[PDB]
Amino acid sequence: MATETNYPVPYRSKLTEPFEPGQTLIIKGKTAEDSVRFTINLHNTSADFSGNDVPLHISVRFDEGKIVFNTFSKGEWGKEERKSNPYKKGDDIDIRIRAHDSKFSISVDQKEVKEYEHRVPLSSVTHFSVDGDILITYIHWGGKYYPVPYESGLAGDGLAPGKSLLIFATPEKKGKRFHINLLKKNGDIALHFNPRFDEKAIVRNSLISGEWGNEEREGKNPLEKGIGCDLEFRNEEYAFQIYVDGERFATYAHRLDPHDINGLQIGGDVEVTGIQMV
Image (cartoon, rainbow, N blue to C red; front, side):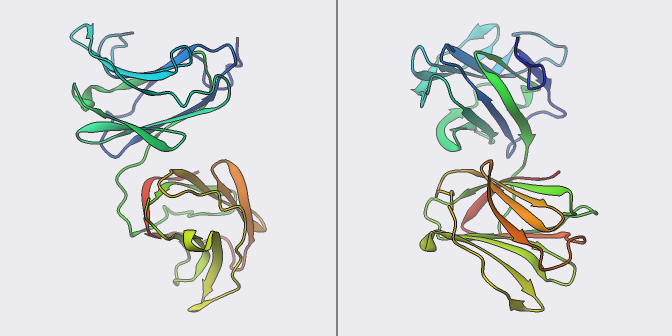
């Protein structure tokens, strides 16, 4: 009888619109030493049909040590496709499903481990459910195919104090570095976040009147080439709180007045899959 606070299993959710290419479904949670398996299903039937048509069925098994993928259509399960389960009976799981026009790309712990070709229409995916021996801690879907270099304004309030900008990205396998700029109307950059793999460091700096300031670097640099990451920039009272994959990576004293930060740029050797302002 886990706390209904988190996502109670069985967890049944309905998408706003059908799952589109470029969108990602993220499922995070915890398992116990007694968990045998849990499932993730991309369902159909807006009329709520528990087990009607299932474009993609994911079964991670600690008893079999494998992750199973299959499709249910025309009232029948099809042929299974298997992959090794980086298992870990007990401890956190991070599974992400990204839709593309010819298949689903599934990543475990932000590492691409499976390409599942569509067998039935992706557009039939109108729901998703999670069940089994798992304690769901986080679920989220969205994103799109973001072109990089990327550049856009931020809604209206922009990244104002008390708000946080979440960016899901994947540094390129053969990339050297990439950057993210949080700018102001005149072109000044309140925050330049520049992961440089060749320097094994993440450079943070500000561009004021065309002149770069003092470089703040050195730190864990928890990023890895080819491995997806969750970047979060929380604009607080005295400084930006920079989170990387759940943990605070650094703090950056405001050098420019917060407020009016409504410019965003992303460049370098990186793939961007999600951007949300909370």
